[PDB]
Length: 484
Ligand SMILES: O=c1ccn([C@@H]2O[C@H](COP(=O)(O)OP(=O)(O)OP(=O)(O)O)[C@@H](O)[C@H]2O)c(=O)[nH]1
Ligand SMILES: [Cl-]
Ligand SMILES: [Mg+2]
Image (cartoon, rainbow, N blue to C red; front, top):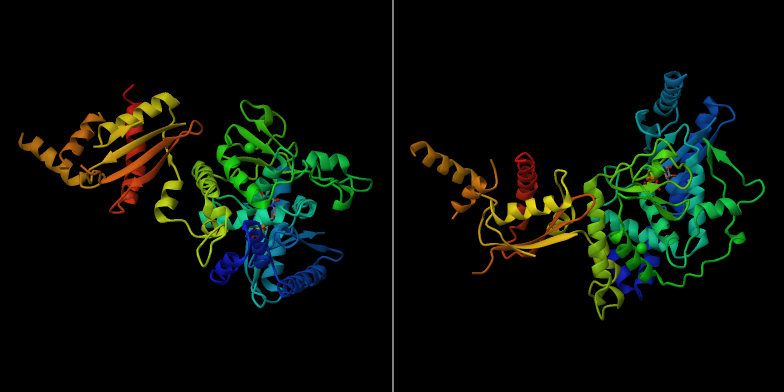
């Protein structure tokens, strides 16, 4: 791993062959599936012992065809407001207590009633496996089946999703935090494939209408109905190759307006959020930096956890990857040994790149006034020579981001023996023609956030400046808000 993978991807043909090979290398082996089935069987046996006539249903990564090595094993267990909440919560503990002291081999057990989808976390020691036991999310079964079906509908889906998943992991865009879940990322890829000029994938609405007899099903008041076999459905007339579709993903999602759009897998379309139209129907829908609607539960934004920082970093990383995707290094192979194609996408992010990709949250303000405020803070209060979404190129000959404490101390001392912007500029002027550090500053219309990226950095002091700006700029903007 991390060695074999690099040389395996370097060795093979074109980018598409690399994506396919990546699928081959990351997916679970037959032994891993054997192990998983065995553990599920154990779970099934003990829970049957406690709950006669109960079924343990595997779902998620394990059955949805997007499985990779080391992925979780998710299990659904199939057997007045606060009352029902707590009844539910009590049952969970029971399940927990069964996992804790009955089924042999599982040690880490933590009940999580406080989650949106209450679950009992567990780990099985001999198999090295770990996952979730969910009392009720029945939708998960169906959306898992939907993802597997999606892979079955077109052969480009799984390579695209695998490549983009590994890439997002490498860019710090996915995980269990404010980052996108793997499910949400997959949904985003599928959404992208739905919106192509010829569509690669159909909308879930279309699937729902195709459906079939006996294939009609509703769970929690939502319609989960779709055809069970891909055989009934006509192929895609979209002829685009894998490398193309990848580049198109990067470009497209880099150019989308995320805050103004609820991306709908049902309609295969972007529903304008402002104002209130998606918010009226489907009560319970959370809107924010990134809005991505579940194919079935329509009150569910699967991206609702994503902070503005993660969304901005997402579109930035996609813009960078789109620029790389236009390069000759991407498309064509290398003669001998060089990193080409998928490899720089799958390689870790540079510290300067990782830092510059994630934007800086700024106090709310009209776009025009905000831009003017920022250029004021750069022009004066900082020694920056600046010049002309919005963007500016800035040049510094000095250490201005550091040494400010001693300088202000000395100036206030001269004030002993002897309000923002210009005052702070004093602090700048007392800190002292090839620019020491030169960088770019960008502001996107919605939501307003500043992207600072390095241009000329001889001494590698850009990150210090970036942290400094992270602290200093919201402060400056803030005081410029209160001068009105
Ligand atoms: O918002 C969500 C998230 C997850 N899920 C359901 O839970 C499952 C878990 O989705 P995950 O985001 O955990 O990804 P995954 O399991 O497919 O891959 P690993 O994280 O195991 O590497 C998904 O397959 C989906 O069915 C939802 O229904 N809604
Ligand atoms: Cl597009
Ligand atoms: Mg998982």
